[PDB]
Each structure stands twice: as structure tokens, then as C-alpha cells.
Image (cartoon, helix red, strand yellow):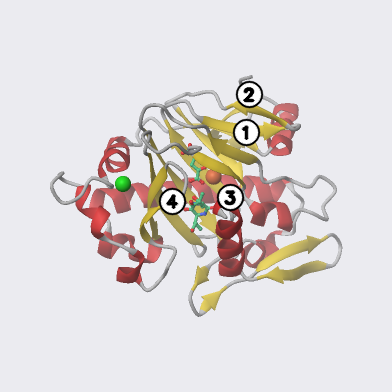
Amino acid sequence: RTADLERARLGDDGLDFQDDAAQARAFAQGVFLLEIPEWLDLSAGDRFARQFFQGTGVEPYGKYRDLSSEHFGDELLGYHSRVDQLEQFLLERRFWGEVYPSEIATLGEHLTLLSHRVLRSVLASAGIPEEDWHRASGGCSETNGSYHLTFNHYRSAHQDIGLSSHKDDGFITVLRTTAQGLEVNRDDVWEKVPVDPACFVVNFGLSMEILTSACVTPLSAIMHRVSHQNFDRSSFGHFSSSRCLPGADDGIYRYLPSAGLERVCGSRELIEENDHEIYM
Ligand SMILES: C[C@@H](CCO)[C@@H]1NC(=O)[C@H](C[C@@](C)(O)CO)NC1=O
Ligand SMILES: O=C(O)CCC(=O)C(=O)O
Ligand SMILES: [Cl-]
Ligand SMILES: [Fe+2]
């Protein structure tokens, strides 16, 4: 009932699995483990995930509870109480420097560059021509995408599932979890994702699935969920999406082999539709 996931590392040539078969399975499963660089400090992010929901009486991060979507002119952002056990703080990179604590913005920058390197290995392995990467990824093949650094707290007193089954919206999710509860549906069976605090969980979102749907090896956005938590749980994730600013939306594309990119929908449109289905 626990998934047997491939483990990878970022090395001198990019994303290194144990062998080519291991990489192929990992990309086919749509989820794998990525070793956390030894120099990367996650302790401030872990603390933010434990505090952000607690209010201005709890230092240094409880005050972010007070920052609702209105403060950002973007309904996606700020503090959100979900219908599941989950409550969240979500912030897109254009606000990190102004709004996040400086050490949290730094964490977001590290993860953006790490995710950038991961995505480029995946795009190369898909055989998409390099000059199409920027438009295909809505800027994420460089550092031009939309990036959400999102903190999660599961309220165990709520008699809900932790987080309903869903696919992420974008291309790459880098997930930091230190406690059980994350499950994946591979081959129509729910399985627990092993907990390894020395690794990130990496998966693909809907944009990756759309982008590669006409390729010889389509990559899937893995269905996942968080089971009902009897004790509190927290985590955070870095989400890479096609640039989805209000007014500057880069679009979602499917790659047609030998032809080029065909536009499928808007990036914000996909995020809004997906969030709608996840919860209602
Ligand atoms: C783009 C942004 C979501 C903005 O609403 C990004 N993309 C995702 O797919 C998930 C969505 C849900 C599970 O987390 C939120 O409940 N989280 C993110 O931060
Ligand atoms: O908390 C987790 O482990 C998963 C969070 C998640 O899947 C999400 O926010 O999209
Ligand atoms: Cl609450
Ligand atoms: Fe998710």
C-alpha cells in the first residue's frame, strides 16, 4: 500500500536517476523522489508551514493569516481556508520580495531554480525541440513562468478528507513533506507516498499532461490526495505554471510532433477550472 518510487538527484548533467529504465518509469508514473541539496536550508519554510495560520500573536510568521486575497488583487493568493481539512497561504513570485519574509523569498528562489533544472531534463527527454521550450512551458523552461510558493496546514479537528483527490495545474510541483498522508493513485489503486525528509516529492501537473498528450510517451499528471489527518500536518510546495498574471497570460499548449504548439486554453483559466473541480 506504499508506492515504490524512483529516487533522483540533480547532478552535473541534469536529473540523474539510477539508470535509463528508472528514469523512464519515474516519468511514466508521473511522480518520483528528488534528493534535497545538502546546502539547502528548509527550516524557515518548515516553520512558516507550522505558523502561517495562527495569527499575529505567533512570531515570526503567524501574521500571514491576516493577508486575504483582497490584499493582492488576485483571488488565488493569500490565506485560504478550504472545504477540506487544508488551509493554505499561497503567493506568486511577483509578490515574494515585497510580501514574504526575506528568508522565505530566498527559499522560493532556490526552489524556482531547482525546478527549472528538473523541467528542462523532462522537456529534453520528451523530444520537444529546444526553441519551442519557452512558449511550451509558458516561461518555465527559463525563469519566466508563474511560481507559487504555497504553505499547507491540515486542521485535524475538521471531519474532512485532508485534501481531495486532484491533479496540480502546472508543469512541475516540488513538494516538501515530512509526515505521512500523501497518497497517489497509480493504476487505479491508492498508495501512500513514502516519507523521506531528505527528499522532495516531484510530480507533474495538468499542463505537463496536456503538453505531452500527443507525444509518443505521454506524461501524466498524477492523481493524488491527502488522507484524513487525526493529528495536525503541514507541508509546502513550489508550483511552476505557465505565466498566469491577470492581463499577461501565456497560454497552455499541446505539442503536435513534427508540427508545433497548438493553444489549448489559458493558464489562469486552467487554474480556476481545476480549483473549482478539486473542491466542488
Ligand atoms: C497555481 C497554484 C494554485 C492557485 O489556486 C498552485 N497550483 C496547484 O495546482 C495547487 C492547487 C491546490 C491543491 O493546492 C490549492 O488548494 N497549489 C498551488 O499553489
Ligand atoms: O500536503 C501535501 O502533501 C500535498 C499538498 C498538495 O497536494 C497541494 O497543495 O497541491
Ligand atoms: Cl481555522
Ligand atoms: Fe497537489
The residue lying at 77 percent from left, 61 percent from top is: 255
Q: Which mark's residue is nearer the viewer, 2 or 4?
A: 4
Q: Are marks 3 and 1 in contact (CB under 8 Å)?
A: no
Q: Which mark's residue is nearer the viewer, 4 or 3?
A: 4
- Bin the neighbour count of mark 4 within 10 Å (Cα to Cα): few under 14, some 14-19, many 20 and up: few
Q: Are marks 2 and 1 in contact (CB under 8 Å)?
A: yes
Ligand 1 within 8 Å of the CB at mark 4? yes
Disc nearer the start of the sequence (2/1): 2
Marks 2 and 1, how far apart at CA? 8 Å
Depth check: give the residue in front, 101 or 60: 60
Ligand 1 within 8 Å of the CB at mark 3? yes
x%, y% of residue 151? Answer: 38, 46
The residue lying at 41 percent from left, 50 percent from top is: 150
Q: Is residue 22 above or below residue 13?
A: above
Q: Which residue is mark 1?
A: 184
The amino acid type of the residue labelled 3 equals Asp
| Position of residue 107 in the picture relative to residue 28 (left or right) | left
Q: Which residue is mark 3?
A: 168
From the image, which quarter does the C terminus lie in?
A: bottom right
| Position of residue 17 in the picture relative to residue 258 (left or right) | left
Marks 3 and 1, how far apart at CA? 12 Å
x%, y% of residue 73? Answer: 37, 74
Marks 3 and 2, how far apart at CA? 19 Å
The amino acid type of the residue labelled 1 equals Val
Q: Is residue 244 above or below residue 188?
A: below
* Secondary structure under the numbered disc 2 in the rendered image: loop
Q: Which residue is mark 4?
A: 82
x%, y% of residue 230? Answer: 41, 27
Disc nearer the start of the sequence (3/2): 2
